[PDB]
Amino acid sequence: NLFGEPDEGIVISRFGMHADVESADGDVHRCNIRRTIRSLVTGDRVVWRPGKPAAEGVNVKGIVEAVHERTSVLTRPDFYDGVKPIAANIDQIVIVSAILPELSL
RNA sequence: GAGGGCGCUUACCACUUUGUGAUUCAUGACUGGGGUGAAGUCGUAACAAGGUAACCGUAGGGGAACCUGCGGUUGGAUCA
Ligand SMILES: [Mg+2]
Ligand SMILES: [Mg+2]
Ligand SMILES: [Mg+2]
Image 1 (tube, rainbow, N blue to C red):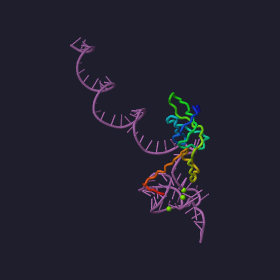
Image 2: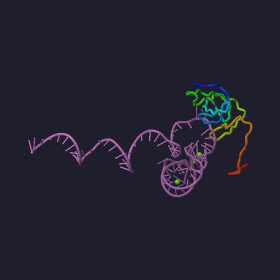
Image 3: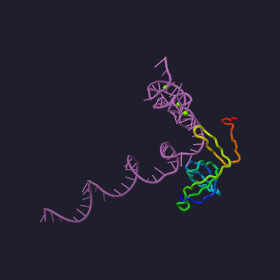
Image 4: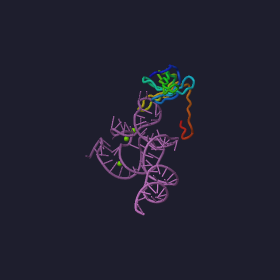
């Protein structure tokens, strides 16, 4: 509770109970998520509020309220897990492989 | 003179010093796991004969669930 400014920022990573949200200038600021969010992926622009600092300058987390629309999505299903998106909102993928241990086709 | 006091010395002994032990708390780089986590990734182990029957004990293997070897049990299906 006692949230801050609703703004647009880029989510750095996903950690289940919380997420890392980069602001509009390059500030690593970890936040938790809203209960009604169906999914949150790496690199998804969101609407979020950075809580409120309890100590002056020292805050713990904020919240991520809403999720914008998807440009792309990477949905891959799995046995006994269902269809799960991995990453989203991307224009180019680079398939990276190595000759070790194997190079399959 | 007898005797006493003072003073000195000795025995006992508190505090105090060194050497070196046992025990206890606080601090403590680092490090060993374990628990609590609905949505995170990795796999599909077990529960049906759960798709190589499972499990216990022991040795080895490898991100991991686990696997194989030896022996035991039915807390196993199908049974003749
Ligand atoms: Mg299995
Ligand atoms: Mg089995
Ligand atoms: Mg056996």
